[PDB]
Amino acid sequence: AAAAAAAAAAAAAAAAAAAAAAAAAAAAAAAAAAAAAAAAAAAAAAAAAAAAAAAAAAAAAAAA
Amino acid sequence: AAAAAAAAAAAAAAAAAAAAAAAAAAAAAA
Amino acid sequence: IEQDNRQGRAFVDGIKQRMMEISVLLKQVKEPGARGSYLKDSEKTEMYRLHKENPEVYTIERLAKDYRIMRQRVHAILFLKEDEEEEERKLGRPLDDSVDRLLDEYPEFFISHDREFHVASLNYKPDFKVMPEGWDGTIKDMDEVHYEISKKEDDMLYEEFVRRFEFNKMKWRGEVMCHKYSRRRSSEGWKITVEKLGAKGKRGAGGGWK
Amino acid sequence: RFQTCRLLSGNVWNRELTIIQRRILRRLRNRKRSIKKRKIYPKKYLTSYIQLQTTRKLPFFYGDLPITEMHRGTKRTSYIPFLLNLETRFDVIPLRLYFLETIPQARQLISHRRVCVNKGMVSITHFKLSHGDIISFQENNAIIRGEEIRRSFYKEILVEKIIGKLLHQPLRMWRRSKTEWFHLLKTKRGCRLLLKSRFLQQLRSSMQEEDLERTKKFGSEKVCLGSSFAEHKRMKRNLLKSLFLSKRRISPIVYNSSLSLYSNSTYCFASPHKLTMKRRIKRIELPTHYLEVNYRTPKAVVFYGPNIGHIPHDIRLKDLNLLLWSR
Amino acid sequence: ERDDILLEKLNAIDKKLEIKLSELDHTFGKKGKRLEEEIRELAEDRNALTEKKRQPLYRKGYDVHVIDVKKVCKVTKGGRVERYTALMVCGNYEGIIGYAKAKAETGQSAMQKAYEKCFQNLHYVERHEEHTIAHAIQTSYKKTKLYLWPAPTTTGMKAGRVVKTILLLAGFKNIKSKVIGSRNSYNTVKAVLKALNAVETPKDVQEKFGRTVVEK
């Protein structure tokens, strides 16, 4: 399982996560050029790829 | 050869029958 | 060579896992007299497109028998996607469609009807009527007399919902609160033969109309 | 309240079962609910016991109104005021059936806030509406409950289900932190679309399979058989007659293919429901005897009235065959 | 497996028949030197042969219907003898309803000692449209009388308790019924049985000419 403080801090993070689990807004689109457009494009594509890859990684680390 | 295949049909079919029979025998536990 | 034809068709059957699933859907359709689909909302915005462009050919018979839905359901599809487009204009190119985007088919049952009145009859009162020995007649079918009463109900249903949704649409722009002006009187009633009516207007007499 | 679940010997949908509540429910559910419901055969009016249990389940389901009193208001037994209040009581039924908690969350809403019907506010909390009724929030309701219904349809149908069905059996204190992580991931409106397009395809395939299981339950294979009655006999004909033609009168590979595909025919059309399953998650049964919403901004006009076999009963068909004596 | 053990028990009993027929047909002569084996193998025959009629107790001789119970306390007065009587009713929701009545020395023991006899002496009731009965009918036991009137599909069961727990798990849903006279238990049972078995459905009334229509 885990420990008392482990689950307690996990609940703390869960509360601080559900407070933000509304439609949080850290997707900023200020890229105004062909060049900056493609740049922020690639940054966001890598960001989402890595987020969901850490996701399936958690999936494996739990399937363990 | 074809007699080997006829007895092979008997073999595989009785095998399947017995396999599913034991399968039901186990499913009757729950 | 017939033998390899045979083996080809035997392979055809062996790869027929899907037949299990067409049987799935057709027995589900059996179950309540309904149809096993969602329309997935692509078909709903698609049929709104279809009918909006072609309100001449795409009747609510063509449309609703294409997509196999309930007629008034289709009607509200039309209305809702329509004003949703009108407010798309309003709220700009931001369009939500968030939850609509869900097209995974685990988290949903959404059983929709295609026929209607298949769960059980209006009643089953045990009662009989005997016909003599030389009946010289032919009996009727019970599944067959069913769906005639369902058709009666269905027609009455269409009529009544049409009328109600209609008045609600005409009501989308009216007055139900504490303010009116109230100077017409709606001349009416004969109480033996009243299929004629009239109104009055304001302080002018009017009449004979409506 | 959880105490009521303890009384009902089971689970009346308390939210956020803390750890000792987990313990006590496992104890009570298994030990008690088994021992009583498993093998007793009491004269202890098991009919009337069942009656109490069901007439006590239902009121929390519809908040807190006394439903014996609903029975009593008419001189019937049941099923009519049932189909009626479920045709609508207009906050507890529809607002929950689509997107809320039927409890005084979805209540008091009609008390103070507005959900104008046909743009008309109906703040009575017990209305009956059918056959052409447009259900719409106000805009200052929308500007919050659009986000609330999104976080519902995802955090409570994607996130919770997905931390379920997996990550589960050994440790739940671990699904705890996994929910933390997936919360951090659902914080992201790009992660939304990527998840729409992620490997959930696989889970939906497995779900199709498990529905096929619960289908074969009661003869889907028997109707598949009857519908392909010839084809298996045709395969047998191939085998036996090509036998009594080629030999004993390519033969070996004729026998190869015939054996394989014929035995596979019989297997796939006679595998009898190896269930053996660990648990079973539950679907959300959306109402399409009522018309959907513009889920963008709530505009969810009704189009019809309800049936009796498509209702969220937390009770099996039994005990409700004692309440609603229906087919 | 059922037939396996049946014919197996038959093998046992057939070796019994063999050796005991041999010994019997030797009547003539000295006595003991056959009677020892007599007693041994006959006792064995008992142990084995009674297991057939033993079987019905738990696994088979036990279907998957549901059962319900009654019980009272009879008396003999040699000193202050006390015993227990008990009733059981089996039903499967499709209508096969049967019952049974037997006695024992303590409650659960009597409940048991019927729990494996309710499944014999079965009578099969014909529930018209899966929810209710074919018509109205009066039927009387010695001094308990009974009245059965159907109801259209939505009322529900309007009956008492001893009669409800029969019309329920027979498979009816919309009967109204009135039992009058004696308010006893074991007469309402067997009153329901003498009643439901009295209904003649249109299948029956085609005891003469005429296809009896249903009114559609």
Image: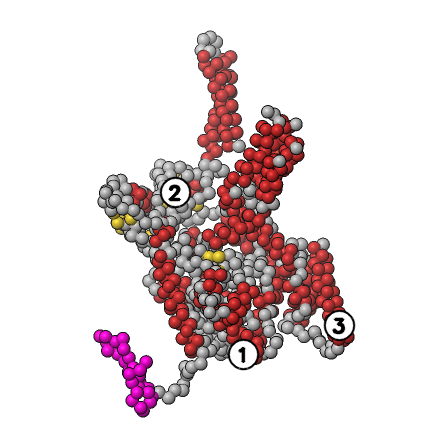
Pinpoint the chain carrying mark 2: E
Cα distance in 3D space between marks 1 and 2: 61 Å
The quarter of the picture where the N terminus of chain A appears is bottom right
Asked whether disc 2 touches disc 3, contact meaning CB atoms under 8 Å apart, the reply is no
Q: CA distance from mark 3 to mark 1?
A: 37 Å
| Real-space CA distance between mark 2 and mark 3, rounded to the nearest whole angstrom | 77 Å
The single residue placed furthest to the bottom in the displayed view is C203
Residue C197, image x, y percentages? 28, 79
Residues under numbered marks 3 and 1 in contact, where contact means CB atoms less than 8 Å apart: no
Label 2: which residue? E96
- Residue C194 on image: x %, y %: 25, 76
Mark 2 vs mark 3: tell me if same chain: no
Dot 3 amino acid type: Ala
Query: Circle 2 — which element?
Result: loop
In depth, the one of E116 and B27 nearer the eye is B27
Give the quadrant of the C terminus of chain A: bottom right
Location of residue C184 (image quadrant): bottom left
Looking at the picture, does residue C192 appear above or below residue E199? below
Question: Residue D6, how many percent across, how many down?
Answer: 52, 59
Q: SS for tag 1? A: helix
Residue A16: where, in percent of width, then height?
A: 67, 71
Task: Say the numbered circle drawn on residue C10.
Answer: none
Q: Is residue D43 above or below residue C175?
A: above
**What secondary structure is the magenta-colored segment mainly?**
loop
Which mark lies nearer to you, 1 or 2?
A: 1
Q: Badge 3: few (under 14), some or many (20 or more) residues near its Cα, within 10 Å?
A: few
* Mark whose residue sits in front, 3 or 1: 3
Front position in the image: D48 or E127: E127
Q: Residue at x 53, y 50 (%)?
A: C22
Residue receiving disc 3: A38
Which residues lie in the magenta part?
A: C183-210
Judging by the rendered image, the residue that carries numbered circle 1 is D139
